[PDB]
Image: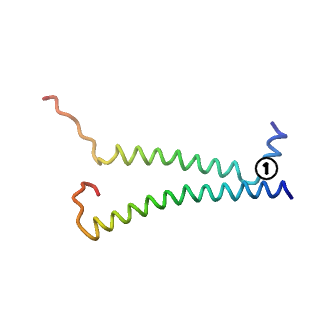
């Protein structure tokens, strides 16, 4: 809606702060999964003998 | 003026709440720094990848 989009600019940077917080959160789960799972440098393979 | 007071109170409450969450993160990092000076600097940690 154009009218609500015009009225939403009067509130300053509420949406920008919300987007910045959610983008930091989304970067944070990538950092979480990288620091949990990617502690190994080179990927090793199991030999066929078990 | 009540509209401006409510808006600025909401902005200050958002600022204080985000600073409280950020201060919790800084407090966790400071507890980690206290642990990493007690164990690393004031000792020798036997924990692997610590």
Q: Looking at the image, which is closer to me, A46 or B44?
A: B44
Q: Quadrant of residue B42?
A: bottom left
Q: Farthest bottom residue?
A: B42
Q: Looking at the image, which is closer to me, A10 or A45?
A: A10
Could you tell me which residue is drawn at 82 percent across and 46 percent down? A7
- Relative to B32, is A24 on the left or the right? right
Could you tell me which residue is drawn at 68 percent across and 56 percent down? B13
Residue named by callout 1: A9
- Relative to B39, is A19 on the left or the right? right
* Quarter that holds the C terminus of chain A: top left
Could you tell me which residue is drawn at 82 percent across and 45 percent down? A6
Could you tell me which residue is drawn at 46 percent across and 45 percent down? A30
Instruction: Kindly state the secondary structure of the residue where label 1 is placed.
Output: helix
Q: Quadrant of residue B2?
A: bottom right
Residue A44: percent from the left, percent from the top?
24, 40
Disc 1: which chain? A
Residue B26: percent from the left, percent from the top?
48, 61
- Relative to A35, is B10 on the left or the right? right
């Amino acid at each position: 809606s154009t009218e609500c989009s015009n009225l939403l600019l009067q509130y300053g940077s509420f949406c920008t702060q919300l987007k910045r917080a959610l983008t930091g959160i989304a970067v944070e789960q990538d950092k979480n999964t990288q620091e949990v799972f990617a502690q190994v440098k080179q990927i090793y393979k199991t030999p066929p003998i078990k | 003026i009540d509209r401006l007071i409510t808006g600025r109170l909401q902005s200050l409450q958002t600022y204080v709440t985000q600073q409280l969450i950020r201060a919790a993160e800084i407090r966790a990092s400071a507890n980690l720094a206290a642990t990493k000076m007690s164990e690393c600097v004031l000792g020798q940690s036997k924990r692997v990848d610590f």
